[PDB]
Amino acid sequence: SRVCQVTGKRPVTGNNRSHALNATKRRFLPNLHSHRFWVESEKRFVTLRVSAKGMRVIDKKGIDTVLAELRARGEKY
Amino acid sequence: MQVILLDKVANLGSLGDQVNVKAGYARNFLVPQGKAVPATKKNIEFFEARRAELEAKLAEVLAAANARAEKINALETVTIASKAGDEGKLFGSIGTRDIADAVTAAGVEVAKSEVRLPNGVLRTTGEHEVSFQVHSEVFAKVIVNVVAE
RNA sequence: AGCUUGACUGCGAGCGUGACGGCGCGAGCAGGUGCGAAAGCAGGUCAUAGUGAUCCGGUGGUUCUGAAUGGAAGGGCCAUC
RNA sequence: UUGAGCCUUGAUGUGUAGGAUAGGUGGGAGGCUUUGAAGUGUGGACGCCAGUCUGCAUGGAGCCGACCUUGAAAUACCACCCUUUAAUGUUUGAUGUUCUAACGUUGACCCGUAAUCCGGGUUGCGGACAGUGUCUGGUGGGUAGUUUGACUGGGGCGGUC
RNA sequence: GUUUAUUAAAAACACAGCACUGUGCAAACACGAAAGUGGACGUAUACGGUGUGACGCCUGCCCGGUGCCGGAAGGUUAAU
RNA sequence: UUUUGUAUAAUGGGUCAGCGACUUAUAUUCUGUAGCAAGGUUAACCGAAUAGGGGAGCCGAAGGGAAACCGAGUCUUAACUGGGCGUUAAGUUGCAGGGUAUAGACCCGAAACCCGGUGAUCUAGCCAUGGGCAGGUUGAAGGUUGGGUAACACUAACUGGAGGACCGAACCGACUAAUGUUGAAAAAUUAGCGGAUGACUUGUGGCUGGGGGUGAAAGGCCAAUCAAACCGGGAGAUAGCU
RNA sequence: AGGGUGACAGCCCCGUACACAAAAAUGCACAUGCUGUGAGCUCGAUGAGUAGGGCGGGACACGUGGUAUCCUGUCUGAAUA
RNA sequence: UAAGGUGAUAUGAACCGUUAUAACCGGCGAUUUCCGAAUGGGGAAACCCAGUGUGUUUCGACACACUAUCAUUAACUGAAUCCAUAGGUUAAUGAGGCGAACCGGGGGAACUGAAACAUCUAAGUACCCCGAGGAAAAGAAAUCAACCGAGAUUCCCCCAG
Ligand SMILES: [Mg+2]
Ligand SMILES: [Mg+2]
Ligand SMILES: [Mg+2]
Ligand SMILES: [Mg+2]
Ligand SMILES: [Mg+2]
Ligand SMILES: [Mg+2]
Ligand SMILES: [Mg+2]
Ligand SMILES: [Mg+2]
Ligand SMILES: [Mg+2]
Ligand SMILES: [Mg+2]
Ligand SMILES: [Mg+2]
Ligand SMILES: [Mg+2]
Ligand SMILES: [Mg+2]
Ligand SMILES: [Mg+2]
Ligand SMILES: [Mg+2]
Ligand SMILES: [Mg+2]
Ligand SMILES: [Mg+2]
Ligand SMILES: [Mg+2]
Ligand SMILES: [Mg+2]
Ligand SMILES: [Mg+2]
Ligand SMILES: [Mg+2]
Ligand SMILES: [Mg+2]
Ligand SMILES: [Mg+2]
Ligand SMILES: [Mg+2]
Ligand SMILES: [Mg+2]
Ligand SMILES: [Mg+2]
Ligand SMILES: [Mg+2]
Ligand SMILES: [Mg+2]
Ligand SMILES: [Mg+2]
Ligand SMILES: [Mg+2]
Ligand SMILES: [Mg+2]
Ligand SMILES: [Mg+2]
Ligand SMILES: [Mg+2]
Ligand SMILES: [Mg+2]
Ligand SMILES: [Mg+2]
Ligand SMILES: [Mg+2]
Ligand SMILES: [Mg+2]
Ligand SMILES: [Mg+2]
Ligand SMILES: [Mg+2]
Ligand SMILES: [Mg+2]
């Protein structure tokens, strides 16, 4: 599903409000992209479904750290 | 993205330099292909520790290489067992090994690669000029005697 | 026609007319003004139409308020849109 | 390639007395030369057609200072500069051309695998485009929720408030 | 041929034929938040949408309005 | 019952028996009544449990002013000869009742709107796999032979067996009339009628689902009432109407 | 207390007040063995794509209001007692 | 615990028992077909059909046991591709389904009220979905206060319509 494997970001719901303040239900989807990360320590690419925010988390922490979070979480990659 | 360059990289900097760069360039090329690393403070301390430890090794090697340059001018004259032919021409020749081994066993531990002769290998009896490279840029001179065995 | 700003500010005994919201008439009192020698007259126009409640917001004023305290924002009050 | 900042470093001056198109302010007695000048033969650019900067070749033992004029000095030379101009170095854009490495592949192939799914891998074709997320202008009876007054010799029309 | 099963079978719908118009294929279009699928194991002599309605003789004028197609200079104009 | 007015030929009731509609909770005010009285009363809770404890609170004995603030006054205005509201009526807590408020708020009753399910055993369209069309006509293309032509054209006989072709049972349909209409039947029966090798008809099973399907298009059909199915729920929707 | 008994029962029956009871399994409690968990001490360390911010929404009694505080779909992004 | 018993309609029959294996009551065991999560595969529930291993004074098929999926772990294996990794088999352990209300969370109406209606209301209600426990959730201040101080969370009464 539309879920970031790094941050957990997922669709959330809310309103479109018109000028006349009519609320209609809507969603806000995360900004997801399947992206291939080079993992040095495993001589391999890992494809993650990540939000752009999630990409910046990986720039900051390093893919090794973030994949370690995936394991501990039981989540497979 | 601040990153610290590993190998030298066009238009950015040399090894160790710190540079800002677009994330996608760092993410999809420079880092995977081993050309740079993030600018984590542990890392920049790593390299500041590196720049300084490297700086110390360069200051002290210069302190060792200068010391040997004071010692080269200290001896300032050397003899070598040299079988000299008639008229003055050496039956053989006096190479860098011959010069090096004189001064090592006469004080200063100069290896032959450090010895620097121009044209000659010295095929004449007499007193000669010899310069040396003990560091990349610090040089000195001994004078060489040729005693006829 | 001359001089002029009473087309004044604060009030108001007592009345009229309204289911109400309201609307009207009012001598007199205080301050200050115009006209008249003076008595006096003037709180718009001979009278009766010419109009839009509240909310929200704008502008000026202000011995009010001011979320720890001093301010400020915002609110009140008075004037007005 | 280019507009707007930067930096080296090079172009450029007709108050008059004159060796004559006097750049102000300073160090200021030797610079400049064979890493090759004076001189003439010509090329270019600027221009007040007075001359100025300047490539090439030729040439081969000089152009030089208080030597006097001029408010201010030697084209012997040197430093921050301005009158303006060019071009190498930089920040941000603008635009374009390529690249490959994100990403796309509903081309071929390999393995998982006696599989027209999927995944990994190879390769070809594209490629920072496409596409998607958030925001934003336009469109939008496709869908949706509603409004669309009262009086009235019935209602509606007309009229009216 | 079809149709209001149960008051209408018809002149209504369809029809072969005609025209306009979209569509270069991962087609347009359609069902689907998506994946997937129909179109089609088709490929412009094909597929969709719209109108007309065998055939014969034919189908004139109007682009101001509304709709659509094309345009880049100017004005106006969103987030930022 | 409803009405200006009903014997009214306006409504409702065949009759009897049983049931069937102004309640309840909490706020609030007034009346009656009781307690205490410038005071009255406690709530949760404690509890020795209808006692007693608990006075946190609430109402009242002070108002005026938007407020600061002043205070039996205050505000208005620079100030009132004054003017507005107040000062000179005892309240409070139970208990019964009258009203109101919030709640279904006196009972019954819509047409409908929303949500989650169940339905293609009827019927629409499609998919796969099977079955069916007595009997009688017409006689396309093609082919052979003959005549014919320079050669084709053409032409006769024969052969051949096309078609949403013709007549007509089964089968599919449903144009007219009578009957029936508390039927034999919630759509038929009788006499006639149209299609009947086709865009035909039919069995078995499958797929499409409700703002959805399907529709040679009638708003037709989707299990005997479809301009939005059925069931359950929001649900006692709402009903200024009867 | 209540019920039953051929009509209404303290004394007919079953009960009730009170007093008692478990071979076995189980609850809960103190005690204790066990495998595991670590106690107190000194010197440290102190939660970053976070707080904050722009855009769109949502939550706070508070409807964008002069609107603090919270959450965050999107773009960003600190200080370090 | 006992002098009466073999549940009911519900008799009868044939029997059991009376001082302690009649019956009756309670604790613990045994047995517990088939369907159903249903779990060897299938399926129109209570049925159809298997593989492997064991057993036959008869070693036939009949009978008995195991064999679903997923997750964690381990052993043995093992590609594209050299190592590796994916994959594959087996074993151990766990989960699955059901069911009142309360409970945390993901989604989330409309009628209705506003005497119409769209902001607003109804209401984070009805409903759908996920998950847990005897309770759940919450919880030891980057909380309040107001210059005095308080000292996590939860619940009740006030503050106050
Ligand atoms: Mg006078
Ligand atoms: Mg203002
Ligand atoms: Mg404050
Ligand atoms: Mg303050
Ligand atoms: Mg784009
Ligand atoms: Mg928008
Ligand atoms: Mg529109
Ligand atoms: Mg509409
Ligand atoms: Mg409505
Ligand atoms: Mg009317
Ligand atoms: Mg009909
Ligand atoms: Mg008919
Ligand atoms: Mg027509
Ligand atoms: Mg025409
Ligand atoms: Mg256009
Ligand atoms: Mg009447
Ligand atoms: Mg009468
Ligand atoms: Mg009657
Ligand atoms: Mg009747
Ligand atoms: Mg009766
Ligand atoms: Mg009273
Ligand atoms: Mg026929
Ligand atoms: Mg008939
Ligand atoms: Mg016929
Ligand atoms: Mg069928
Ligand atoms: Mg309701
Ligand atoms: Mg009702
Ligand atoms: Mg009796
Ligand atoms: Mg901290
Ligand atoms: Mg914060
Ligand atoms: Mg304001
Ligand atoms: Mg089975
Ligand atoms: Mg089988
Ligand atoms: Mg099964
Ligand atoms: Mg290998
Ligand atoms: Mg369970
Ligand atoms: Mg309403
Ligand atoms: Mg449980
Ligand atoms: Mg807990
Ligand atoms: Mg303190």
Image (spheres, coloured by chain):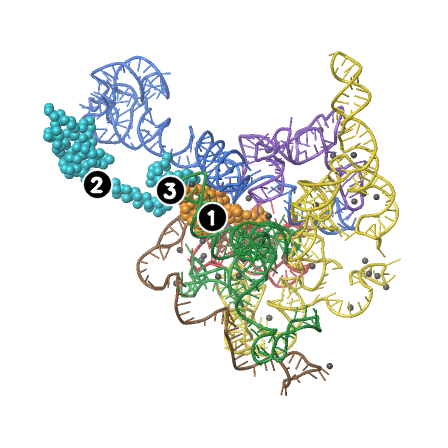
Chain colours: A orange, B cyan, C red, D blue, E purple, F yellow, G brown, H green
Q: Residues within 10 Å of mark 2 (few under 14, many from 20)?
A: few
As rendered, which of E15 and B16 lies closer to the eye?
Answer: E15
Position in image of residue H32 (x %, y %): 58, 62
Provide the residue designation for mark 3.
B37
As rendered, which of H94 and A23 lies closer to the eye?
Answer: H94
Q: Label 1 to label 3, Cα distance in Å?
A: 26 Å
Q: Label 3 to label 2, Cα distance in Å?
A: 33 Å
Please state which amino acid type lies under the numbered disc 2.
Ala
Provide the residue designation for mark 1.
A76
Same chain for labels 1 and 3? Say yes or no.
no
Provide the residue designation for mark 2.
B63
Q: Residue at x 30, y 45 (%)?
A: B49
Q: Residue at x 38, y 43 (%)?
A: B38
In the image, residue H106 above or below residue D114: below
Q: Residue at x 35, y 45 (%)?
A: B43
Count how many numbered circles sit on residues in the image.
Answer: 3
Answer with left or right where residue B93 lies relative to residue D36. Answer: left
Q: Chain of mark 3?
A: B
Q: Residues within 10 Å of mark 1 (few under 14, many from 20)?
A: few
Please state which amino acid type lies under the numbered disc 3.
Val
